[PDB]
Length: 205
Length: 335
Length: 61
Ligand SMILES: Nc1ncnc2c1ncn2[C@@H]1O[C@H](COP(=O)(O)OP(=O)(O)OP(=O)(O)O)[C@@H](O)[C@H]1O
Ligand SMILES: *[C@@H]1O[C@H](CO)[C@@H](O[C@@H]2O[C@H](CO)[C@@H](O)[C@H](O)[C@H]2NC(C)=O)[C@H](O)[C@H]1NC(C)=O
Ligand SMILES: [K+]
Image (cartoon, rainbow over all chains, first blue to last red):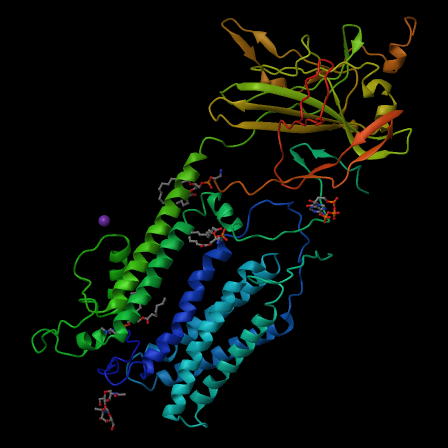
């Protein structure tokens, strides 16, 4: 006997009735984006840019502001808060159930660390002059957003009560992810793959 | 409160500061350039991080691939050994847990392949992800192998070790003044095609408006064939006489105590074992220019064989010298 | 073959001619961007022209 991400109950993995209309498969799918973002954003930040182009004395905190930076910090702090709430609800529910049922909160924890890594990646890639990499981040959000949606709609088909704690708590994540996606899009113009001026201006200490 | 800005600190490393630069960017090809050159402490981590990441990622992919095909249901729930006979419909034989998928990804990528977890012919997506995982594994393997060989190629070169004396001198040789430092070498291999150049850095206005702020003249080093080369095994003394053409010709004994001079010295050449060019540079502000002091004999013929005694590399002894100017000394005989 | 990036020696857009140290002088500006230094450097300036010879041969370039 050990961890059972789908509940240690037979037929809890019986996918005969429908392909994605399962309580745990949706959770695992939602988990996947974090276990992709961490493993595509750990070493890139680890092996920083160390090549020599012009000099070593760069303007400290050169581009202190970034396009749309005002929302980012507060929005991601709210994302951390809602992840905390989700993990709390799961963990409090856990003690009533029989088996471990890691599907309750493992995605929440993985998303917590993923969001913290996202904040670190944003700050370490924006302050230094390297926005061509930032495009990668955008992909994550899209992926993550889709999975989050893939959850919520199904719940409506199951019609969980609006007054229930879990459904209400999990609802806001989709909107938070959408706002974050819009924030990432709005700074899409200066640095992107093509057809942009991509104007270069240095900023004063 | 700061002292006059120095062009080159004692450890080379020209400390200029270029600003107003047309900052291109990074191009994402800088990351690989940095990665090929790291201190060995890191390249035993990025190796482990890359391998372990790729393994775990493909393990989760196998887990979901098996999970969505209903295999895990057939293994876990249906009869353990006797009550159930496999329908052969499974996607990846005998992987009924996540740890099983981990021990399958290790097999499928490190080319171990124990054979207790075969690949059947049912699930096309499984074959697709097998092709993709194998390709990714080979690409990562080749990149890491090339990185390790590159960082084994650079095990010969360590650091430039060519030692100039602390402070220079100015003395009398053959009835004429001079200006001497002391170069030297440490490691076993000699230098090949070694060359020496002496530049004096100054702020020299011109009678026609132009005022070059930091301008660098070149001055010859003493040699009986007018060749800037030098062949050194024991420390030499690269003198450079002063004459009307030379810029130090107007230096003075007292004015040098408050004067704007900057005699940088650069030395180039290759090393036989490495076969790589190299150079070393230093500078001598007025504060560390003595006067009258001459360098000390260092080589003494012992009973058996010659000995160079580093114990007194930069020691100097006072000796006769006039306090007049170069132009004073060369002005007239009686002068 | 990844150590290389590209050329990094920069010239002035325009020349200059003036009087220095009493006589006419031709100028040009040279600068560098790469942090690593450039050892054993050398420069050469050449005039390219269509010429004439008393014997008659003409070299176009
Ligand atoms: N601040 C700078 N940083 C990097 N490179 C520069 C800078 N200024 C000029 N250059 C380079 O010097 C060359 C000629 O520059 P120039 O003196 O003509 O300035 P400019 O008139 O602004 O140049 P351009 O017209 O190309 O913008 C150009 O090829 C350019 O790449
Ligand atoms: C988990 O295993 C239990 C074992 O009792 C299953 O029990 C279900 O309980 C409801 C309550 O009415 C009934 O439908 C049956 O007693 C069981 N449901 C069936 C056979 O469909 C339970 O099915 C398992 N969990 C889930 C989500 O199916
Ligand atoms: K093998």
